[PDB]
Amino acid sequence: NEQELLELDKWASLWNWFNITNWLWYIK
Image (cartoon, rainbow, N blue to C red; front, side):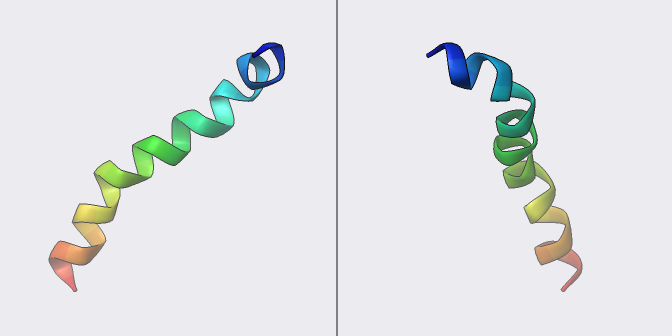
């Protein structure tokens, strides 16, 4: 728990990628 609490910024971009993955796949 304490380890991931600091890595939360690294995970923030990971789940956020599922939002932009639709853009690149849409134009492709």
